[PDB]
Image: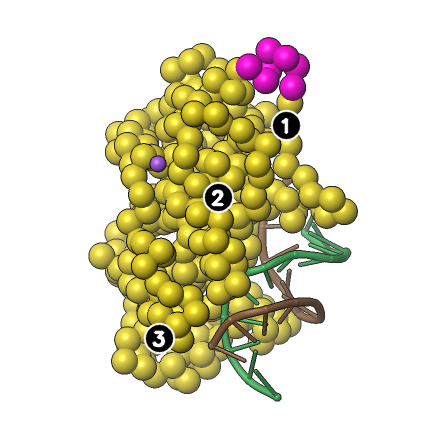
Chain colours: A yellow, B green, C brown
Amino acid sequence: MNYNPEEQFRCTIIRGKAKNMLDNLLPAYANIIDDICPCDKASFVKDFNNRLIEILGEETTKKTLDNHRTEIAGKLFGMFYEDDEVIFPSGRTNKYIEDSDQPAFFKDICFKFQFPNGMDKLDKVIEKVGAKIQIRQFPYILQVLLTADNNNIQLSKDDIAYYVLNSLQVLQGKIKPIEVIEKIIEDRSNDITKKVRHPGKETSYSMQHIREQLNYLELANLIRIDGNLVKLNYREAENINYIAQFWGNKPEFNAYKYDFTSEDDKKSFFKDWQQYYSNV
DNA sequence: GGTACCCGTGGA
DNA sequence: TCCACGGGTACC
Ligand code: NA
């Protein structure tokens, strides 16, 4: 009730590195990890980077290699985890190694994603927790898209940006998808269109994490993003419906049971997040 | 000072 | 416009 999208909140995900070359990089990440793990952390860094540089090219800096390892293979794709000082392949990696199913890899990412989460830097976690954010955003997006179709309208990427993925109230879990749809219909009837932009900032700051969230849903074969519209792929109706049905659920991983001024909890938060996100 | 997400920036 | 390098930044 009282949905007001005017309350806006930038809520990022990790910036991508693997989209352009995904069909080479995803097998590389997985095979590197499967081959060299389990192993000690020190060995992992060296051996991972030495293999990845053969894919990315000899001119690639160590910093870039490290960032691929930590940001993408580790955090965003959840491909390995640590336990008692040894690095292991994750459940998600193990499954992909058996089935080679790239859409299923991304379906699982979309199923598990939430805000808040343990991908973010601690200061950003504290911000999101301070704002009372709690949402499973991919179930939610899918339900918004179903509800749009049920009401005979179609949504643009900008609609999903402003009304959903940058809306504080939606991200707080306060708003039903039908409220979003009804508001979009009213706004359009008043010739109001909306976009997400930030003062003095380039469009990547405002939109790249929004576009890229949608990309993962497209890689899962659940939607198709064209120049104008974001549309469901009803060939995958069974998966769309299964995932959409979680739209009203609290996040499976509860960020609010951690004390982020406690040194022990800070550490448990990130470890427990990785176990939830990466493993079965 | 080191590490590792954050994000300005520009080639593709 | 997309998206990723690698410096920026702030936690580690
Ligand atoms: Na709710």
Q: Which residue is mark 1?
A: A194
Q: Which residue is mark 3?
A: A264
- Rendered image quadrant of residue B8: bottom right
Which callout, 3 or 1, points at the residue further toward the start of the chain? 1
Rendering coords of residue A2 (x, y %)? 48, 25
Asked which secondary structure carries label 3, the reply is helix
Asked which secondary structure carries label 1, the reply is loop
Depth check, front residue: A4 or A203: A4
Chain letter, disc 3 residue: A
Q: Mark 1 or mark 2, which is nearer to you?
A: 1
Q: Can residue A117 be spotted in the picture?
A: yes
In the image, what residue type sits under mark 3? Asp
Rendering coords of residue A146 (x, y %)? 38, 23
Report the quarter where the N terminus of chain A lies.
top left
Distance from the alpha carbon under mark 2 to that under mark 3: 31 Å
Number of residues whose C-alpha sits closer than 10 Å to that of mark 2, classed few (under 14), some (14–19) or many (20 or more): many
Distance from the alpha carbon under mark 3 to that under mark 1: 43 Å
Q: Mark 2 or mark 3, which is nearer to you?
A: 3
Q: Which residue is mark 2?
A: A213
Residue A188 magenta-highlighted: yes
| Marks 3 and 1 belong to one chain | yes
Q: Which residues are magenta?
A: A186-192
Residue A239 magenta-highlighted: no
